[PDB]
RNA sequence: UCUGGUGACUAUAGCAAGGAGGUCACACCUGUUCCCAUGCCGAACACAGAAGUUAAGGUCUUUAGCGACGAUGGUAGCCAACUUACGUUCCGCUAGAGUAGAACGUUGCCAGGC
RNA sequence: UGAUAUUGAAAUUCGGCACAGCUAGCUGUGUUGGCUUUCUAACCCGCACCACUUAUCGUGGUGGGAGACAGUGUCAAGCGGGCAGUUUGACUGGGGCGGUCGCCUCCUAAAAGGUAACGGAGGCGCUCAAAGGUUCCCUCAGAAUGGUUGGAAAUCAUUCAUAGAGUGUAAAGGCAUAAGGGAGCUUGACUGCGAGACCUACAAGUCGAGCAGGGUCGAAAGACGGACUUAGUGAUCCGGUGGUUCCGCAUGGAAGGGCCAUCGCUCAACGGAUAAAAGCUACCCCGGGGAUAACAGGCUUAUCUCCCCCAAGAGUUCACAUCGACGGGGAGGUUUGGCACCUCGAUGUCGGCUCAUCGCAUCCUGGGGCUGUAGUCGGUCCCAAGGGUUGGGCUGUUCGCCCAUUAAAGCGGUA
RNA sequence: GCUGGAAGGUUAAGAGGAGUGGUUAGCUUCUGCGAAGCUACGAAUCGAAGCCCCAGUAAACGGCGGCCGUAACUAUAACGG
RNA sequence: GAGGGUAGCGGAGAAAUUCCAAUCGAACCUGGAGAUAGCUGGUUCUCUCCGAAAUAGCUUUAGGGCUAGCCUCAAGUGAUGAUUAUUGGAGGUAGAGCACUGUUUGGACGAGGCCGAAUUCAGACAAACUCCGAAUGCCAAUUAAUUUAACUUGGGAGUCAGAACAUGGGUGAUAAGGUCCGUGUUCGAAAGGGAAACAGCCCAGACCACCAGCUAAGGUCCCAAAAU
RNA sequence: AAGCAGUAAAUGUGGAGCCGUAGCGAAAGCGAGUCUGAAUAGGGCGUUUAGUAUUUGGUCGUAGACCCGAAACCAGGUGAU
RNA sequence: ACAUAGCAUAUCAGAAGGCACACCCGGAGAACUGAAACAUCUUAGUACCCGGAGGAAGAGAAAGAAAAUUCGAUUCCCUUA
RNA sequence: GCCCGGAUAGCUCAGUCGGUAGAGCAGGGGAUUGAAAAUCCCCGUGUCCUUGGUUCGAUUCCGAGUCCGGGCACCA
RNA sequence: GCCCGGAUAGCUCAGUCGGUAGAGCAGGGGAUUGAAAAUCCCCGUGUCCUUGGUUCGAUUCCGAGUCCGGGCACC
């Protein structure tokens, strides 16, 4: 309250609106997969209970900022473009 | 001393601002200026 | 206890900051402001370009020098060499 | 060296006067068909030319009378110190302006021809 | 005061609208509002009689009078200090009064920048389709000298003109390379931007080399993202119009939002409290201040009271017996003020009675000089505080005028 | 201000319902009509008192001027503009 | 005199702001209620270290606030901070001057039919007049000598009522212990010694003890230390 | 966390949730980078890893929020001796 | 005049009043204060007043939530925040 | 910134729905009659606001236009 | 000591928003008619208050200025 002079949040103008459906993918990075083995699957029933992700709002996107380093097989919700190259680099399908 | 806008005839909008000082040229004023998304020079009409 | 006359003017302008803004010798950079005036008290020289009737500003890198080349006129140059 | 072309030098270089020549190089003129054009006129701009002329421009040698530059000494002001309520002194550094001594009738780069 | 409900019947008309037929206008012809009346069952009668009952309330019947109006609800307009919540700016050598409130330019400002006052001077709330961009070319107001008209000066030439003119606007800084004046073309008075600076509490504010797309002018090199600069404007919120690859609450559309471009404010008290606002209190009330006045102390001496120089002149003659134009220099702190230093958790304020006490710039009395001093009176000046300094009319008076006296009816300080 | 006046302008609820938009039955199938239904809006026209308009009222509120010139010496004006 | 009525947005009034349970420009008693108060007064045990401001901008704002400025602990960065010599620079005051716009008193100079109308010589004046133009300060050397700061981030504030001297100035009357800016010092927030006493002037900064010595400002016959 | 057991035992279970591991933009959406944008040009904000739970201090916010003080307002009543 | 208001006897114990008015449910309902003033707003549907019950009153057996696969009366506690 | 009314003898009004311009006040000249005022004749010029278009033809219908009267004026 | 209105034929008023001066009373000369008064023609000079500046141009806008009318006047 600047003392009668109107405050800093009256000069600045407002803009925006949020949403009603702003689907927040739980963004698991690609580096975190470099801990387990046998290459069977990754799974919204398993990728929770290996402690990696918790309370995924909707969808579990594979953003790629690590290194795959294994011929792994995924089964995710939906992908990123560069990380979908890394899974098909060493070899493995999915179900988007 | 009247403000008036110029109209990109092929662009289908209004984009510029001028100052037509009223009774010294009361007619329509048409120039050649730039109008993007068409990347040419269209006539712009004093409406 | 008598009613004194009314003053007339008061009423000053604000100010503008003028004069030199860098000085002879130091090292300037290619956007900086050398000198500024409401007229032409210092002409530009090589590697210094005018603005809108003000703000002699250096084109490129270097150090600055003040200099005269007439009997009254004065100019500013910047030499990038070192 | 000298004549011309382009540079730098704060008019110390320029104006003001006076004498000297030639056009090998600038000018002056000979015209307007063409190149081009004068809110008009080819005086100027451009073009075509070479019989004349050094009077003029420009060049060169004198004149400090016009401006310009300009020292040594002084005096006013003044940062620091001291004393004092005086429109002040006193001591220690920097130091003009005007005015005089005067210097001065340009200097030097690079090109093409003598 | 209207609409519509309670709220019913009948007639007269005057309409617009839907159709026919004829001469823009009339007949029938159906919707369809109104307008006047006329009844009668609703409703009302502080309307007389009868019963509850012996009772002016009330309930019930009977006869009368009004009557589809009123009275009542619901919605809508105008009246409305009768009554209520409220606002009524600040700056200020205390306050109201007068004037001011933001931007631009000087000076004060003390050779960087900055720097106040109710200090001194001026402007603005725009204007220009060319007075913007480019390529070329030209140089001025004046001073002379003559020349149909004569402004002293509206054109024409010649010569000496360094800026003494001009720059749309007020001033300073600039400009004769023009940034001034003409002539040909044209829209860069563009779009997306920006390294880095200057200023600055913040929000703002200006200056930008170069980068891409599209150009204009020019032979080309280059210039151009408004006018020689610095003024000419106004946050947010909310709403309007034109686009939109964006969201659009089951899904598909819409309504609405958001972006991007733009308009609406003398919100001028100009960082704008709100969409909307003026006065008196001597009937005053509370919280505070000597931050801030009136009375009185203090500082200062403009005015004020006294001296004082200089000397023109007056005094028949002689400047100085007395008088002193024009001009200057000081003491006092008694008047009128200036400043706000102490006092607002109270320092009682004018005159008069009571009672004094102290200075001397002396009113009487004492002592002298000098007189344009015959004597008696009188003018002027020096030393002198010991003592004296009147009774009445008038007004609150101070002051003042007036009457009758006296040796005289002194001027002041002491809150 | 108050009373009196009745024509005209100016109005609100309400009565009216010319039309414009959204939507899809069907449809050219790319491409606008949209019948109908339901909804969002709503046009002229009608709709009083007030305010405009006219006239009256001061023992209602309120109001009740300036400037020059002139007379048988001067003075001022009965008077004039 | 006895009974009775009218009650707070109210009542009564031969009208005065009078009266309503020693009162009243709207009575009293509870409850909302610990109303709000940018305003006064008050806030309690001790010692070490460091220690300011009274200004700027904007406000229904001038005795209030918010931000920057000035202090403080804590981390960092760590040679960037301070003076001095050297060189190079920006700008137009004090001074000077009349070439510039302006103000001036003197001499000759022309410009009708007895006093005046452009220029020239010799002099002067200026905050808004400068052909000139210093002392100092001010920014920068990738400069060298000496010393101890500086800056970035993050917690905690306080100040926005200043005063007198010394000088450059406006206002005032070359008046004030006046007011308003610059720039220094001291007081505020600083005790001692001198100025008879005396916050602001002159010396100088108190950690405590001692019956020790030199010295500063002012003094040396006596009160009162020191030279008749 | 609530609850459920338990010397009103502070210990056992309860993984609903919160914060953090990835940001950018109004949003769709995109991702170690997006956003404006015609641009792979230039910019702003990010990337290279330390957050988290409880508590002792310093300070803010909502509550009366360092104490003590006003005239004054609005309800509900008692009073004409 | 037919009956009804009205009028006269006999039975009945239904009501009224009080409560801790602590808690609850409906009727009616202020202002001081905050916004640095103030009128929409907020203090708050809070305090006072009145009415009716209970040991608990109110709510309540979907014309609901939801959007995937649906599960399911009301109340209350924690998170969503 | 928005919707209408129109600029009709020198003054005031009239029709001015495309072939289709009127009044009264004023002015001038006669008459009156001692001289003016009245009073009575006889007269004229309009402007159909700037300008283009649907035009056999526009004072007349559109709008590129100047000026003023009636409502605008909303919760910035 | 303060803010406005202005000095407009000899008298009274008018526009007097920078190129852009009007009326009526008065005066004079004709006519009238026994003579004056009326009455009717035809005429003129204004002053745009002293003075400077923004001035293609100021009666016109500022203020160095004289006079008077409207409010000042506060505790
Ligand atoms: Mg020739
Ligand atoms: Mg009855
Ligand atoms: Mg009232
Ligand atoms: Mg005040
Ligand atoms: Mg005052
Ligand atoms: Mg300066
Ligand atoms: Mg939907
Ligand atoms: Mg839906
Ligand atoms: Mg009285
Ligand atoms: Mg006093
Ligand atoms: Mg004196
Ligand atoms: Mg006094
Ligand atoms: Mg003071
Ligand atoms: Mg006190
Ligand atoms: Mg006391
Ligand atoms: Mg008393
Ligand atoms: Mg004596
Ligand atoms: Mg005595
Ligand atoms: Mg008597
Ligand atoms: Mg319809
Ligand atoms: Mg009274
Ligand atoms: Mg009484
Ligand atoms: Mg209290
Ligand atoms: Mg409360
Ligand atoms: Mg210390
Ligand atoms: Mg001087
Ligand atoms: Mg001076
Ligand atoms: Mg002083
Ligand atoms: Mg000072
Ligand atoms: Mg100190
Ligand atoms: Mg002492
Ligand atoms: Mg002693
Ligand atoms: Mg009684």
Image (spheres, coloured by chain):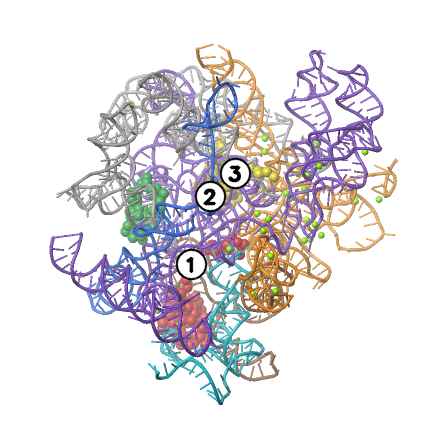
Chain colours: A red, B green, C yellow, E purple, F blue, G orange, H brown, I cyan
From the image, tell me which residue sits under label 1: A15
From the image, tell me which residue sits under label 2: C58
Q: Earlier in the sequence, mark 2 or mark 3?
A: 3
Helix, strand or loop under label 1? loop
**Which of pointers 2 and 3 indicates the residue nearer the eye?**
3
Q: Residue at x 43, y 70 (%)?
A: A26
Give the vertical position of E294 relative to I38 (above or below): above
Helix, strand or loop under label 2? strand
Q: Residue H4: percent from the left, percent from the top?
A: 53, 83
Label 1 lies in what chain? A
**Residue A95 visible in the shown view:** yes
Helix, strand or loop under label 3? loop
Give the vertical position of A43 relative to E153 (above or below): below
Depth check, front residue: G36 or E330? G36
Count of all numbered marks drawn on residues in the image: 3
**Residue A39 visible in the shown view:** no
Label 2 lies in what chain? C
Q: Which mark is residue B28?
A: none
Q: Residue at x 48, y 37 (%)?
A: C42
Ligand 8 occupies quarter: bottom left
Disc 2 residue lies near ligand 6 with CB under 8 A: no
Quadrant the C terminus of chain A occupies: bottom left
Depth check, front residue: E150 or E192? E150
Depth check, front residue: E289 or E55? E55
Q: Is residue H75 left or right of residue I74?
A: right
Q: Dot 3, how many residues are within 10 Å of its Cα: few (below 14), some (14-19), or many (20+)?
A: few
Q: Residue G122: percent from the left, percent from the top?
A: 56, 19
Q: Cβ–Cβ below 8 Å for labels 2 and 1?
A: no
From the image, tell me which residue sits under label 3: C9
Q: Residue at x 54, y 54 (%)?
A: A3
């Amino acid at each position: 309250f600047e003392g009668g002079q109107l405050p800093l949040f009256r000069r600045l103008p407002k803009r925006g609106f949020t949403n009603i459906n702003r689907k927040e993918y739980a963004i698991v990075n690609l580096d975190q997969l470099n801990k387990f083995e046998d290459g069977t699957e990754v799974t919204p029933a398993l990728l929770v209970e290996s402690g990696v992700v918790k309370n995924e709002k909707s969808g579990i996107k594979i953003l790629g900022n690590g290194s795959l380093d294994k011929k792994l097989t995924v089964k995710a919700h939906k992908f990123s473009a560069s990380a979908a190259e890394a899974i098909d680099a060493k070899g493995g399908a999915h179900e988007v | 001393r009247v403000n008036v806008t110029l109209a990109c005839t092929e662009c289908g909008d209004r984009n510029y601002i001028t100052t037509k000082n009223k009774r010294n040229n009361p007619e329509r004023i048409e120039m050649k200026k730039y109008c993007p998304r068409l990347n040419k020079y269209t006539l712009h009409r004093e409406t | 206890k008598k009613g004194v006359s009314s003053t007339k003017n008061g009423r000053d302008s604000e100010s503008k900051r003028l004069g030199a803004k860098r000085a002879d010798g130091q090292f300037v950079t290619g956007g900086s402001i050398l000198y500024r005036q409401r007229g032409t008290k210092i002409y530009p020289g090589e590697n210094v370009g005018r603005g809108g009737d003000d703000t002699l500003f250096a084109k490129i890198d270097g150090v600055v020098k003040f200099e005269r080349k007439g009997r009254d006129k004065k100019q500013v140059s910047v030499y990038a060499v070192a």
